[PDB]
Image (cartoon, coloured by chain):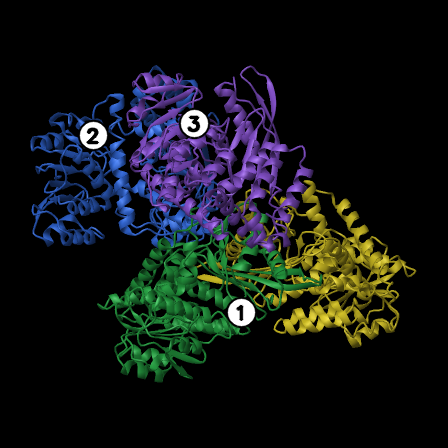
Chain colours: A green, B blue, C yellow, D purple
Amino acid sequence: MSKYVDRVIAEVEKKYADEPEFVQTVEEVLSSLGPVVDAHPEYEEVALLERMVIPERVIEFRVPWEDDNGKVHVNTGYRVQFNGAIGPYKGGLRFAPSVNLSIMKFLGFEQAFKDSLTTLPMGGAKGGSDFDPNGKSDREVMRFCQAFMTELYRHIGPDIDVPAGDLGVGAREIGYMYGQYRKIVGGFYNGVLTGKARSFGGSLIRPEATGYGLVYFTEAMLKRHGMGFEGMRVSVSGSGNVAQYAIEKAMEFGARVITASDSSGTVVDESGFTKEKLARLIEIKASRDGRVADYAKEFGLVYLEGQQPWSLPVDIALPCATQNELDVDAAHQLIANGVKAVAEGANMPTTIEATELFQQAGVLFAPGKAANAGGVATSGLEMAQNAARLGWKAEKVDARLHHIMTDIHDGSAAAAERYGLGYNLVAGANIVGFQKIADAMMAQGIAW
Amino acid sequence: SKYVDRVIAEVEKKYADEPEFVQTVEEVLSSLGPVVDAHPEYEEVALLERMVIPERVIEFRVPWEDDNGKVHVNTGYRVQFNGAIGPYKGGLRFAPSVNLSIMKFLGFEQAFKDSLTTLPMGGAKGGSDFDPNGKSDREVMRFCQAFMTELYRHIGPDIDVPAGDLGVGAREIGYMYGQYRKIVGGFYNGVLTGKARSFGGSLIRPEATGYGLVYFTEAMLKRHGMGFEGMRVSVSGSGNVAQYAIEKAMEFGARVITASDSSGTVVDESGFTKEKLARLIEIKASRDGRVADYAKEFGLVYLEGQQPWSLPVDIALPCATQNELDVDAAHQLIANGVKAVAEGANMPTTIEATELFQQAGVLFAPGKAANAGGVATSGLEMAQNAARLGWKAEKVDARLHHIMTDIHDGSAAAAERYGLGYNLVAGANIVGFQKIADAMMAQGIAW
Amino acid sequence: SKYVDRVIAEVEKKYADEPEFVQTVEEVLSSLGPVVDAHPEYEEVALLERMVIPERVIEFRVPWEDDNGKVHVNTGYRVQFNGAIGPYKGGLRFAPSVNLSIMKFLGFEQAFKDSLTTLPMGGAKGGSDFDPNGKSDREVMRFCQAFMTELYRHIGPDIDVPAGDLGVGAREIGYMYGQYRKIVGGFYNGVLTGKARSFGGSLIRPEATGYGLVYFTEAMLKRHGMGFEGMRVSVSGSGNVAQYAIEKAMEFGARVITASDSSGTVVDESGFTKEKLARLIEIKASRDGRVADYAKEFGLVYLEGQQPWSLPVDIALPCATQNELDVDAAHQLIANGVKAVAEGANMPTTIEATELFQQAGVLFAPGKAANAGGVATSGLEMAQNAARLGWKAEKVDARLHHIMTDIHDGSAAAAERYGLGYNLVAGANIVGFQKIADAMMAQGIAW
Amino acid sequence: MSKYVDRVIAEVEKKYADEPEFVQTVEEVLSSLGPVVDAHPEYEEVALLERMVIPERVIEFRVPWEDDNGKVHVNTGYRVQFNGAIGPYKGGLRFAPSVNLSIMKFLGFEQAFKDSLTTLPMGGAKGGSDFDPNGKSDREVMRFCQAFMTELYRHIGPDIDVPAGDLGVGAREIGYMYGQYRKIVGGFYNGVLTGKARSFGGSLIRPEATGYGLVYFTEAMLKRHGMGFEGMRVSVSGSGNVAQYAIEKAMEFGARVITASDSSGTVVDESGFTKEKLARLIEIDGRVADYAKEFGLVYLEGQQPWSLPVDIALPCATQNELDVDAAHQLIANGVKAVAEGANMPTTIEATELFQQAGVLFAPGKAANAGGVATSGLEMAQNAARLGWKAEKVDARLHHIMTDIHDGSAAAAERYGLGYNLVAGANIVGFQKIADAMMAQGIAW
């Protein structure tokens, strides 16, 4: 019951009042699951929701370290192992001074479901430190990592906990942490972390992953309704990681990607992007202050200061820039111009009010939580070193990523079709994400 | 073998209190006499004397609380019989009968069957004298939890992977894996097979034995130029084995014209169809759901207490129980011109009826090899958990198939090598023993 | 000390939502200003900034099952605060009010009582928001098991050694130990303290606090002329602390004249005898017999609804609860010229009572150091367990005596010293802190 | 070249004076990395080299044992865990009375680069004992092996360090060792070892591996240059493991192999080898001249096969078996490519002339790494946990050899050496290790 759901949300808001960021995330997540909790009288008989909201295991640890001048600092370290029903705990590490339990708990709670979402066996967890990488030297971050990892190693492993990057943790940090890991444990065990370099491998397709996968996912949404990217007008916002590779894949399915935006303006390319065009576009978005305004003028294209792409007549709309970048009166123009599909590349670009609108009437709509997910999936593909094999030549990793995206779509639809709907992919994606944990947790008994 | 004879005797005297074990030793060794004969090195390293003593046996007290808060006491068992070719493997059994003797005979056999499949599984059996009979879902949970609190230390993905058996299904697994993951603090889902899909169970698990039986007989058939296409098939039993034999049988072109419960046989002669079989599954899926109900619903014959061996068929797939096919049925099938019989249930044909199935030269597939798609796929489960991927239903099935054809090809036809003609029984049995003898020798005298 | 003030301030900001802990770092850190000033080295290696963050904090889920089948879930805590001078030590609290703030404040202070003892014990505190109140004998069991099923992987005789507190008694510790033994498969009975005699508990444990109190005040009393010999003593409470303070004072020729419960004080002008105590212990352990029945049975004086503080005496030992010897009552004592007050109970002296008590110049042994009987003999338990045999009461009692004495001495000794003359508060604080600081200085960064 | 390299080489010549073999290897390795170390000033900043030349971990241990007569002997065992950045420690074990730390360290050091050179995630290490298996009974090797593993088991494992075979150690000892390993650790964990019997984890194509890869590699080389084995006349020296299967694979690529040799002499079949001719030879006890008679084929005593005009030359016999004068005839006669099945069959003078034609040359370091690649394949199978058909292993071995070629050719290319396989083979071996040590920081 949402009687059940509502009452848990209550206790949490009281009990964890001083952990705000986590309280909203519990609320924002458990209130989508009403109907599903409804279908399953048995959940509350075994106190499922109550158990799900308390992490399995939480670790906090002192992290003393020394700067390049020999001053000794001390930060707190965190690894919240939220849920391990459907795999080893998985989730990134975040080194940022805001980092606290509440934040690690909310990130962790979410990671659980996004992990289940992928269909690969991955748990839910987050971790990090108030350590602030800002203006730290390499050596200093190296040493911070070493200390961090000196305590963390005992709680993780290829079969226990596989952490990754995030805010302030990248392949550089990952490699230092690993360096220390194997120094201590005494063997290879490269599965203990994802995000690694290709040398101790380290998966190909990882930078591609998130954007490649947005296109893969929407090709499937397009499949169920006898459409495809093939010769369709695609408009894209953003110009970072997702967008670069959104465009790349989009243009292998033979679409005509006509836009790319940044913080300032939008580029419009009637003929659509090509390999040479896009490549140069990257070179400029890697040379701050290289602006998309320059790409336009260098190539002789119309640019649009202060404007988003959404006023463009397109078949497919792919927002991969920022949150809330696509508002009610942007979907009004998009729909009016005959938008067929809209899919989320960034993190929650479409506003709630513009998701209604697209959803009824017409318009497909891929939710980012499922649609972006490529990166989250290929972390699971990095594990597949358990295979102890020469990564995969990238075609082999792309193929898998392609199939995986297809399945997150397939089962995301099936989830709704299941609980009285049909192509609400939003409720995808919620359910399925929760269903998999749920079922595992029911099967495993009253232990965790 | 005067050697084989001697071991058998020694075991008879030493384990007299262990009849089922003693029995399964003579029953198996007596068959390896030609093999042992050709390998005079075996006696030198006391091979047989080693193989019949299990590497390791663990027994343990299992205290638990029922729903009334009353304390009970059972006994857990895990007999890790032979770990030479893979990590110990074999199922768990909860039944009041259970003791060392039973645990050991199932375990010894497990070794050979696991070896047969050509996947790197060893051989072990386990369980408790706990009795799932009229215990609450929850009672069974507490017992599985108490069971695993001791057992976890002896088993593992690389060490000993148990599974389901009499008394133990995905419900019992799952409760067990859960207590296990809670104690060790890891995922390591490769510790158990027969799991639910959500934490690493395999697709094709439900359908494994059935399918595999069809894959195997097809292999037996196609080596005698025949096949399932357009052939008349009869199936006894209406459980999971029978269900998926039929599903595979018709996928191959076959026409399947029977099924049964301990109530009676049902005849269709237009053959089952996907649509037709789907309902039987539902009906026979509890409760009181009977075969006649399936027959009525489709206006098909229902032989009240008889079994399907009367009907003339090209191929016969017994999937009911032990001894369900004696000399009576044997002559009938031979008379009516049966081309092949193949066991999906546990040794369903009597020894006497394996006859002289010699006559008419009837193609014969022993359960030992033929009903082994379940155990072969537990390997496939083990392998997927190792890859930390899930394989599609297609993938798992394509490899269950390739396996089964191999269980046939080399496990029957050598045989052959030792000149027993075309004797799948003895020729796939030697194949099981050989892989273990091979590896044990290589590994010297430690175990 | 500015450094101590900067750390304090920084702490108030970062852990504002953790009041108890902020207040406790404040209380404790602001009394070592001198020590820190005598040691610039500490700031060079950020000793204070390190000491306030526990080395390792564990939270875990604890699902458990009601006597009638419904699932509850609580949260489990273990704060391993400091392990420089030994294995994490510190009890476990089971109480609905528990949280990290509380576990942190208790842990932090436990590092110091612990160090204070001179035994190799580090500091930690733990428990659950579980509430034992209204929970059956067998629900506590099932909970303890679920609790330990996680906790075991973080503790052990050489790592972290929990004990009791609020909601954790010999009962709860036995259940926890039981589960530990079953999970890890050995004895390792040094993993907990507060154990029953049968599996490694310690003789002298029940008497630890009250015996220790007496021992401590004696050393205090000698460095200032006198001793319990022939002195008049007032004790409050009828507990293990009370009873055994009376017991040990009598062995020092003292004349102990009071004892109380929630319903008043008993006055015995002739003093407690060894027979008189025995018969009071019998009673006050037998709900619902009370202090009164002890009086009416011996024709002693009974002051209903009041405390032994108006009673003229040389020596007052408050052994009941917190803030039980307050402001206006602190005067009577002083009026009647009490020479020395020593607290066996937990912070029974109001921050006013300790005006101060000198002012007056009256000897004062703060509970921090004086009631460390139990904390010390728990170290003795760990000890005997490691030795694999059980010391006689005489022997534990002896070791407890030299320890307490060593506690006084070091607390006065390096504790002056430093300036402040004979201040047993502060002293107790500086020696605690000192040992840890030295050990942590010796082993570098990190921890 | 560079001064950073010369310095370290000097430092090592000094400290490990009594470890001649080691020192030879280090100077022989670091000498050829001049351009790489030059192009990376970040190495020296964090003291690469100086680290790399010290083995991460070294284990030595007493190995007491009893012979068939009750006599206690006592030998010394070694496991040098040289480098572990790119995979778990990996390398064979040697049983020979010559064995010491100097040898172990040298073999181990090269091993780490041969492994990296392989693209598979395998580290570097060598191991063994001064035990001498000659004139020892089966049972004495078994009991020694057990004594050996009773100590060694604690330092290795599927994830940690995975030994294999070498001089003194074949499947027989690998089994005895694994036997004791599992008796002690009490799980399966095959993959602790390689060179196993197929019955408890071994791989198919293992016997084939070296020789196949030799052919796969050079055929990659040839494609890059618009050629292939198909149509060509090919000469082989030696007639053992590598020799045999080099001919089998070559034959399958449609090439006419027209020679075979041994410590004695050569056979000349200008009509070419056939599946069946290659069948007889193999002979054991009995030499090549015999197979020449049994087939009426022209035999030549004492002399090598290099005087025959061929399109490809495949030395698979010994060290320094291609001298200069030989290399001169070869070139004179039209040789288009030469490649090394053996260990260093070509001298630097003869390698020099070849690359100074005209002539495509595949360094044995890359070209004979078939068995090292397929031993990493065996680890992969054991992880999987299934066997792969002989055809599957081969397909994968085929691709890996091509990668080895591409990666090598690409590395010489990056550094402007423009298709010198010899130099690239040295560089990608160092490069991968270096990249990973750089990313893992200062810990090892």
Residue D226 x/y as whole percent: 34, 45
CA separation in Å, label 1 and label 2 = 68 Å
Task: Locate residue D200: give its quadrant.
Answer: top left
**Mark 3 or mark 1, whichever is nearer to me:** 3
Q: Is A69 placed above or below B126 here?
A: below
Crowd band around label 3 with a 10 angstrom C-alpha radius: few (<14), some (14–19), many (20+): many
Report which residue position mark 2 lands on.
B350
Residue D284 x/y as whole percent: 39, 19
**Mark 2 or mark 3, whichever is nearer to me:** 3
Labels 1 and 2 positioned on one and the same chain: no
Q: Is B233 placed above or below A202 here?
A: above
CA separation in Å, label 3 and label 1 = 57 Å
**SS class, disc 1:** helix
- Identified by mark 2, the residue type is Thr
Report which residue position mark 1 lands on.
A102
Pointer 3 chain: B
- Identified by mark 1, the residue type is Ser
The reply to whether residue C263 is visible in this rendering is no
- Identified by mark 3, the residue type is Ala
